[PDB]
Image (cartoon, rainbow over all chains, first blue to last red):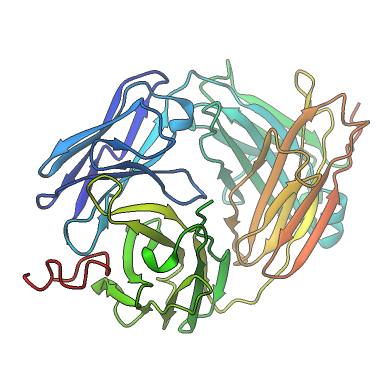
Length: 213
Length: 226
Length: 17
């Protein structure tokens, strides 16, 4: 078993930049292979034989190397290139894959659009209250969301979810969801969500009073 | 036209057994040989084995011994993998793949299956509740309202949220599910729309949780917060 | 030494191995 190791783990790349990832092997390998994988779908044949491009792959993708040292390289980075790239060898049985190089696109700074959503009336009937804060199409990923309940900061009662880097723009979206018992929820008035992000000229608070609409 | 279709997703119980399909079309089955790759957040992509449907000849990765056999059918153009004695170590996506020993000068994974996600646990199937995330004033900025659907307390993965019935795809974000304290999953699917539309255009989110066999369609009714 | 493609498993180089 040849252990294949990739560098870097995360490649930050601005649009239009020339970047390069490397695949290193435990022993000599005859040829190198590369896949592009976007979360949710199967790995896509990208490079077959260190040099050759699988069908469909743009010629901005280039590839090189011999012995144990190989390099996939993108001459001008594009938005749709955001994916994880895995190298793979056939030489030694069993065929083994790199741990992958994740290409992250460093687009310009975009501030999220921020929205808060009160618990629906149907959920309250069921005895639970979920308030959700939405941060839309922002870059970079680093975003800080902070729940205030009647001005008291909250902790331990929310979970965040982040989408993957978008194909067209290079933004993320995130949801922070606060869960309270129907009873605890009615013990308070002001439910507020406060976002800090590099694109916002200042931290933003979206709030509401319970039962106003 | 050379598709490699695989089964969607499976719930398996701890220390049980599972057979997953991998059917082929667009090429002579027996003239190419079939592989099986495991994917997990950790340990990444791991080859498991292969089989040549010209006879049923195999080959097995040591790491998956006593748990990964590759049987092959009659001319239903299909390969199979059975996993046995499943621990929560086996929760994974399982790809099947086809090899052409020659595209230029090397053996090479040409086309891939969609991947069968396996969840190992003894927990009972459960259908989600669907709650509206209502658009209003708090959802409007520069003539765009956000709205959504909260898909709550279900097990196992996955669900699928389409809006209006695939008629609304632009600007949709279906968030990855997150495991709650309860052992049950939750997600939100949101979308942005012209706020001038809210009053004329109807927004319905179609929720399908195949495991529990439950479909729900929720009309997301806007609110008037002036 | 078994090849990865069991189509190559016959005896093209496995026999010699």
